[PDB]
Image (cartoon, rainbow, N blue to C red):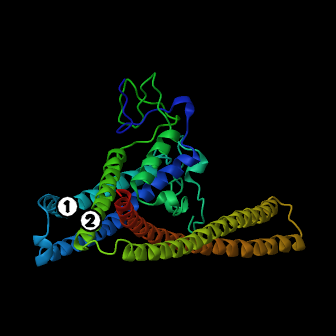
């Protein structure tokens, strides 16, 4: 056995087709890989900002004639360890970001080939037996919908969600859900699909075949390098936080440490209120897009019904027995009335998506800023309270 679905397709066990949610999970991975270039580019700038601030502090602690001579033997060692540790980040960060963008593109290219041609029989291109109808259904509005049908158009299936942000955690769960719902091969008769003629084990026409996974290796590499950037980015901030506490002479046991903390709470609450306001409002736009898409389907159903009734009259007309003039006028007027509502509903669902996408992005920026406030609050909560334990313990030994 030792079956490998990475480079071969197999007849799915129990006739298991690719379900609707299976395409959904695939499209989230495609959207996860797309944001890698944006994620890496914004990561490098944030890591570089930290290691520049910290090293500038180290160009003041050395340049300070009082701080250098009052340093201890043991603290200078780790201080130059921390400075050298952060430089290690910047030095090897460039090829980490180069290898992550390229690995994402190799997976994105391979996934797009799967999304475009898995359900499409390649014997008006027709569907094969691999997919349920849901798998290639335009879930959101798509003008110009025929030439490429039965291909899974991802940016008309899934929109920017919480789980569509390029992070290791989000990428980790997406792969697990895909393995949860993927079509699973048959493990008792090795039945290789694809007309490469394995001869002894060629799969006969008309059975569901599993999804090829050549992107799978590049997906893991992409996610692992994203994980390294997040880990490296947090390590860089610790170097900067370390440098400030060493550059600062550790003054104002609680005078300025409570002052920073009292202010830290103010920004933390304000940004959280700013974050929670845009968070709730983004969910309002989410309802208004589903509320508008549901009407789009209702109008498109109603519009399709009137033109079939009108067509049935024409077939009767060619069949000798015609319908009256008023009946002929009624059907065309009903179609016009049903087409007007149809074309106005899809316009409404076209704009509602623009509303959510803009409102969703404002959620992201609000959450990112509200997380920067949370760190500063927890930096002041540590620098002050841990210091407060030393002043309290002074009075204790008495």
Residue 37 is at least partly visible in this image: yes
Q: Secondary structure at mark 2?
A: helix
- Who's the residue at 30% across and 62% down the image? 233
Camera-side residue of 229 and 62: 62
Residue 358 is marked as: none
- Who's the residue at 66% across and 66% down the image? 287
Camera-side residue of 59 and 224: 59
Asked whether, in this view, residue 129 is left or right of residue 123, the answer is: right
Reading the image, the residue beneath label 2 is 242
Query: Quick one: which residue is furthest to the top in this view?
Result: 188
Camera-side residue of 372 and 136: 372
Reading the image, the residue beneath label 1 is 82
Residue 392 placed where, x, y %?
39, 62
Asked whether, in this view, residue 144 is left or right of residue 91, the answer is: right
Crowding around mark 1 (Cα neighbors within 10 Å: few <14, some 14 to 19, many 20+) is many
* Residue 251 vertical position relative to residue 199 in the rendered view, above or below: below
The quadrant in which the N terminus is found is top left
* Residue 58 vertical position relative to residue 234 in the rendered view, above or below: below
Residue 372 placed where, x, y %?
42, 69
Crowding around mark 2 (Cα neighbors within 10 Å: few <14, some 14 to 19, many 20+) is some
């Amino acid at each position: 056995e030792e079956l490998s679905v990475a480079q071969k397709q197999y007849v799915t066990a129990h006739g298991r087709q690719l379900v609707g949610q299976g395409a959904t999970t695939l499209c989230t991975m495609k959207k996860l890989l797309d944001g890698v270039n944006s994620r890496v580019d914004t990561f490098e700038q944030q890591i570089l900002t930290f290691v520049n601030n910290a090293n500038a502090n180290f160009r003041k602690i050395s340049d300070d004639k009082v701080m250098a001579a009052s340093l201890s033997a043991s603290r200078l060692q780790e201080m130059q360890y921390m400075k050298s540790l952060g430089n290690s980040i910047i030095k090897y960060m460039g090829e980490t970001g180069k290898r992550a963008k390229a690995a994402a593109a190799a997976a994105s290219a391979a996934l797009d080939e799967v999304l475009k041609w898995h359900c499409v029989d390649r014997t008006s291109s027709t569907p094969n037996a691999n997919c349920e109808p849901n798998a290639y259904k335009r879930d959101y509005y798509y003008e110009h919908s025929d030439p490429h049908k039965y291909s899974i158009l991802c940016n008309y299936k899934v929109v920017s969600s919480t789980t569509t942000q390029t992070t290791f955690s989000n990428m980790e769960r997406a792969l697990e859900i895909w393995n949860q719902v993927k079509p699973k091969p048959y493990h008792m008769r090795v039945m290789i699909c694809g007309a490469g003629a394995p001869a002894h084990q060629a799969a006969p026409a008309g059975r569901p075949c599993t999804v090829l996974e050549n992107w799978l290796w590049n997906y893991r590499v992409t996610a692992h390098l994203i994980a390294k950037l997040e880990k490296d980015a947090t390590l860089a901030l610790r170097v900067m936080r370390y440098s400030e506490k060493v550059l600062e002479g550790d003054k104002e046991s609680l005078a300025q440490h409570e002052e920073r903390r009292k202010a830290a709470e103010a920004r933390a609450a304000e940004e959280e209120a700013k974050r929670q306001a845009a968070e709730k409002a983004a969910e309002e736009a989410r309802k208004a897009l589903e509320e508008a898409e549901a009407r789009r389907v209702a109008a498109e159903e109603q519009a399709e019904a009137r033109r079939l009734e009108a067509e049935k009259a024409e077939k009767a007309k060619e069949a000798g027995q015609p319908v009256s003039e008023e009946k002929k006028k009624m059907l065309l007027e009903a179609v016009e009335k049903a087409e007007a509502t149809e074309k106005a509903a899809e316009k409404q669902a076209k704009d509602s998506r623009k509303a959510f996408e803009e409102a969703e992005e404002e959620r992201v920026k609000a959450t990112e800023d509200a997380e920067a406030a949370k760190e500063e609050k927890k930096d002041a909560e540590e620098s002050e309270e841990k210091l407060k334990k030393d002043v309290e313990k002074l009075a204790e030994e008495l």
